[PDB]
Amino acid sequence: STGSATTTPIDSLDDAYITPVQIGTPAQTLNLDFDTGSSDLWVFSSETTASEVDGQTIYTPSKSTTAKLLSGATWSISSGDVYTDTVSVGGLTVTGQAVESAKKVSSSFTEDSTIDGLLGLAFSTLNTVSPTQQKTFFDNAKASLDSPVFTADLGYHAPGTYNFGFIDTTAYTGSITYTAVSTKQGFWEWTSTGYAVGSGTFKSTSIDGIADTGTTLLYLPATVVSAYWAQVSGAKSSSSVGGYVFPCSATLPSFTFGVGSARIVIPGDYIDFGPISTGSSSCFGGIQSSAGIGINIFGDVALKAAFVVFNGATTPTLGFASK
């Protein structure tokens, strides 16, 4: 089996991407945030505190003939109980998928009406269901997939594609470079071989990080991020804003990261996240320091510059191609 679904930016900044997902019988279609940095499938539901719902499409398990309460199971990340139900992505169907129903949701989600929930695609060891931990959609699908892979092809200010079970050889240029993955923290964790700023020379240096479609920006060590922003006239780190900002009049340099011997180039425009407030001439930067995070994160800024293969074979790997 295979599946293929279009993913769409939620706003003009590519702050996140939503992908339609069919849940239940008859289908209830929710727009979920596919997140390779977490491992829960959770949704706004008919059980979510009414005050905390503001425009989202909710999952109603009582209207689904295939929904079953997973008795005693709870989750907490935003929290609630758990159902099993039929879940389909882009034509690919999983039966008995754990669907985690929000009783309560953070204010951050209530405020963002375009995201109906999350679909986690990290390793199932990070799943928060208790007392019986649950499998991700990908893990459940693996048995039936033609190949145990999914690919992320995120667009820049444009729709993209998530594919399951196959690699679309028309979707990238050149070859896919594969690199080792550590699952020890439950993430798609890998080691970049270095970086370059604009047309500058490539610096060979190991950067351990995660491929995280659920994170908007690129978070790298302070040394690297300082070298980048030093090439932008007027750029500075602002404690009031919470990161690097730059004059909206600036032209940003590209940023290159290494994948083995290969190179992925992030165009400068990808690093522009626009005015910090309406009318401001200060703009927010898309490359930020990981120093207060504890881990480097190859978020959407980096990932959308590439065709990315998440290989969930017994020895997992990550592949990157230019496109």
Image (spheres, helix red, strand yellow):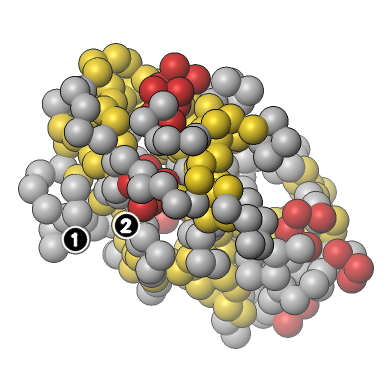
Measured along the vertical axis of the image, is residue 115 above or below residue 308? below
x and y percentages locating residue 96 in the rendered image: 57, 61
- Mark 2 element type: strand
Q: Is residue 261 left or right of residue 57?
A: left
**Residue corresponding to mark 2:** 153
Which image quadrant for residue 85? bottom right
x and y percentages locating residue 274 in the rendered image: 53, 55
Q: Nearer the viewer, residue 279 or 139?
A: 279
Measured along the vertical axis of the image, is residue 84 above or below residue 206? below
Residue at (69% x, 30% y) in the render:
239
Residue at (57% x, 20% y) in the render:
291
Could you classify mark 2 by the number of other residues whose Cα lies within 10 Å: few (under 14), some (14-19), or many (20 or more)? many
Q: Is residue 152 left or right of residue 276?
A: left
**Residue corresponding to mark 1:** 171
Q: Is residue 283 left or right of residue 204?
A: right
Q: Amino acid at mark 2?
A: Asp
Q: Nearer the viewer, residue 257 or 51?
A: 257
Could you classify mark 1 by the number of other residues whose Cα lies within 10 Å: few (under 14), some (14-19), or many (20 or more)? few
Measured in 3D between alpha carbons, the distance from the residue under mark 2 to the one under mark 1, in whole angstroms, is 8 Å
Marks counted in the figure total 2
Mark 2 touches mark 1? (CB < 8 Å): yes
Q: Nearer the viewer, residue 88 or 144?
A: 88
